[PDB]
Length: 58
Length: 58
Ligand SMILES: O=C(O)[C@H]1C[C@@H](O)[C@@H](O)[C@@H]([C@H](O)CO)O1
Ligand SMILES: O=C(O)[C@H]1C[C@@H](O)[C@@H](O)[C@@H]([C@H](O)CO)O1
Picture 1 (cartoon, each protein chain N blue to C red):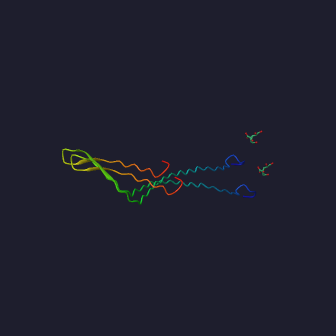
Picture 2 (picture 1 turned 90 degrees about the vertical axis):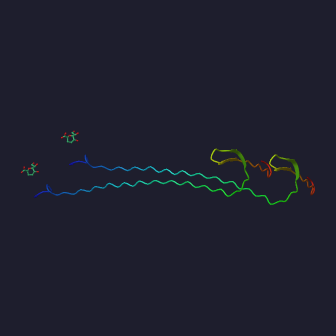
Picture 3 (picture 1 turned 180 degrees about the vertical axis):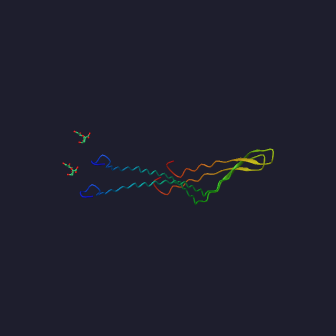
């Protein structure tokens, strides 16, 4: 060890960060009167309805 | 490792952000007297009505 033959110095680093996300929301707060389309074998009713409103410009 | 042969340094990044939205609202707070148009087989009434108001300039 007379010289710096044994003198040693070293550093090392490794950092990793990963992220991920997702969202999906929906809301509906109306009331619509529909009409029966047909009666199924079990008695369930197929209902279809439509409502058109022309407030102004569309 | 005498020289910088092993000396290493690196960085990397990847960021992504996506968004989306939509809204649709409507309101109606009137009163209109309508007239029956015809009587359906089940007794339902087809009602049609119209009201015209000329406040001024239109
Ligand atoms: O004993 C040896 O072998 C050495 C001692 C140091 O001086 C070393 O560095 C080398 C030099 O390169 C000679 O020129 O010689
Ligand atoms: O032992 C070798 O092969 C080396 C030592 C370094 O000096 C290196 O860089 C290369 C240089 O390119 C020679 O000119 O030679």
